[PDB]
Length: 261
Length: 261
Ligand SMILES: NS(=O)(=O)c1cc(C(=O)NCCO)c(NC2CCCCC2)cc1Cl
Ligand SMILES: NS(=O)(=O)c1cc(C(=O)NCCO)c(NC2CCCCC2)cc1Cl
Ligand SMILES: [Zn+2]
Ligand SMILES: [Zn+2]
Image 1 (cartoon, chains in turn yellow, blue):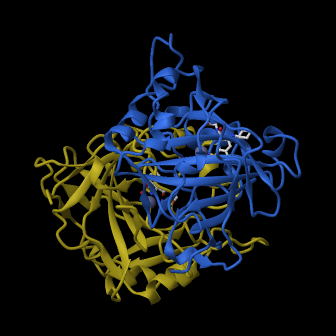
Image 2 (cartoon, chains in turn cyan, green):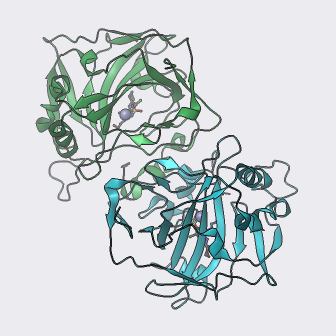
Image 3 (cartoon, chains in turn brown, orange):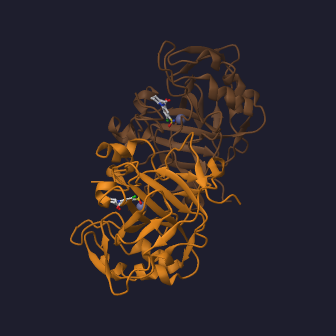
């Protein structure tokens, strides 16, 4: 039911999904008044992100984004529990306005945003169970700007004509997921927040990398024109565009940075 | 009922106030890709703004803002219909993040924002009746930034002491409300939108002046710290801060400007 536009859009999510009206919501605007350096934010290490090219990973249109399932041997090292990968997906704008990141930086949107969702595998047996527990999830967010062609992102994008409708699935050969991350991953923003989509559970430890990556105008346009939120046979199709939430009030939180300056 | 935080905050307004999840919602980000000069946008004329110094006007803390009642002989001339004044009020942030305008410009908040609310007195008998009707309301918005002391805003701010708690009421002697407007009121942004508070009716013609006004650092801090949104004898007092709505999605639409330069 829920959407990003019209009667069932984000100002109405809380009618069905109470946590969407609760505290600790994401995304937010990352701006100077609410930033504070924290020297305890040491580098993350990305383990098992180089997925074998001889293996396949399932790509699905879930009616709200395109998501790639990830294996649980892929994990982050450096947080207080091991967080194992479960899926990645994206958020984007539209062909005439390619400004669809969720997080903003000093009030500006980026073209798009990648989220790599992980769950606390030390405590829970699956990501669905972790998603409604405190700090159950950890997301890596990469801000994407319009720039050079990016062959690594194209390993996902080149399959989109294949998952155009809700519920369709495709196989993507493995590739090195770390190639989707930017430069200087040691520099990031950290804060406690939520899923940015229903059910909006306040259970996410966010890491937003300081530096963006680039993908080209043509790759953005392919992303923004390939997909539909509706099933193949729906008589009222809806293009999957503008699938980002507006930024949320901070509710007195601060965002911690691993960089001073 | 409704608040700007906690579980009765803006993502939940649409539960009781369905138009808050509907079309034409305000405020919005005024950014360069959506601006279009319109030579039809000629200067407004502010008639009856020089309020009698021998009359007193009711200032209230309504638990959401500080509001000054205005008389219906005060009006805007230059729109299709005459719009007569009914009240003015303000929105602001807080001392740790003093960026509480409702509209943004190229993604940036100003420190605060004044709204002078008018209703279509040619079509309707009073503001209450107009507010949910076609062409019902027109708001003048002034963006406020910290700078010089402003004696004209002090004609309101010197009374904040007497309206500290919700429900409290004071009298302000008439003064020239045009003094609250910025330079070059010929230069403005114009679009059709909504109340930025419940009930969020889509019945407002917005005029946001291009140029901000200044108030001193001490005036801005007094506005941010003088008021409480709770009644005086509430045993859990809450300071009135951050009383602005987040910006709303605005797609496939333009904001018209009276200025091209
Ligand atoms: N955007 S986000 O905040 O990164 C986020 C999104 C989803 C999600 O798949 N949303 C459906 C619409 O695409 C999610 N889903 C959960 C479901 C339960 C299992 C773990 C993934 C977890 C997260 Cl953190
Ligand atoms: N912010 S705004 O969009 O300028 C706006 C706000 C209010 C208002 O007073 N909200 C209450 C909380 O302070 C309003 N109230 C109406 C009530 C019915 C009579 C006319 C004024 C009309 C408008 Cl346009
Ligand atoms: Zn996401
Ligand atoms: Zn207002």
